[PDB]
Image (cartoon, coloured by chain):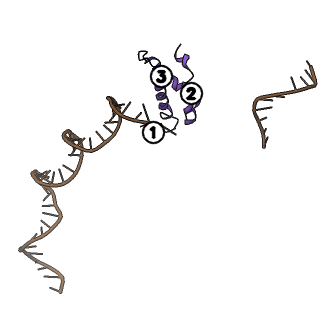
Chain colours: A purple, B brown
Amino acid sequence: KMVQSNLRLVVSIAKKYMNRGLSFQDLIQEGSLGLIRAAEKFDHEKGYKFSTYATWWIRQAITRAIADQSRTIRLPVH
DNA sequence: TGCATCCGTGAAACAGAAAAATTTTCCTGAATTTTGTATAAGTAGCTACAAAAT
């Protein structure tokens, strides 16, 4: 009831990579993945909203997808 | 219900990490020649020799 509760914003992020590559939907997922992870690695004790932390993990997730594939010959993401 | 529309055809992050890989080293081991080396005769040579054709 939180990961989904967010939903939007992650699409505002993923959509930035919908044109970068992969696929709007493809992205969305990826984020989602992240979303999760964040969604729980996350600590309301530091107060400031997940908007300044959830979006972190997202981004991460994503990048690791158009770089992890979307190329049909995987190269050292590094 | 013939008669609408109406499917869809043929033409970009990073630093930090670690862990992998890999890969150079080794070594080694062995396996594998060569050579030594015997080896063992037999030998095919070879060297005089002899009588009898230049």
The residue that label 2 is drawn on is A12
Question: SS of the residue at dot 3?
Answer: helix
Chain that bears disc 3: A
User: Which residue type carries mark 2?
Assistant: Ser
Q: Which residue is mark 3?
A: A54
Secondary structure found at label 2:
helix
Residue A74 location (% of width, % of height): 47, 37
| Chain for disc number 1 | A
State the residue in front, B45 or A17.
A17
Up-down: is B49 above or below B27?
below
Identify the image quadrant of the C terminus of chain A. top left
Mark 1 and 3 residues: CB-CB less than 8 Å, in contact?
no
Separation of marks 1 and 3 at Cα, in angstroms:
28 Å
Whole-percent x, y for residue A61 in the image:
48, 27
From the viewer's perspective, tell me whether residue B41 is left or right of residue B12: left
Q: Nearer the viewer, mark 1 or mark 3?
A: 3
Residue B20 is drawn in which quadrant? top left
Q: Which residue is mark 1?
A: A75
Residue toward you, A61 or B45: A61
Rendered view: B17 above or below A6: below
Rounded to the nearest angstrom, the CA distance separating label 1 from label 2 is 27 Å
The residue at 48%/35% (across/down) is A67
Do circles 3 and 2 both sit on a common chain?
A: yes
The answer to which of A50 and A7 lies nearer the viewer is A50
Q: Position of residue B26 (x, y in %)?
A: 20, 42
Amino acid under disc 1: Leu
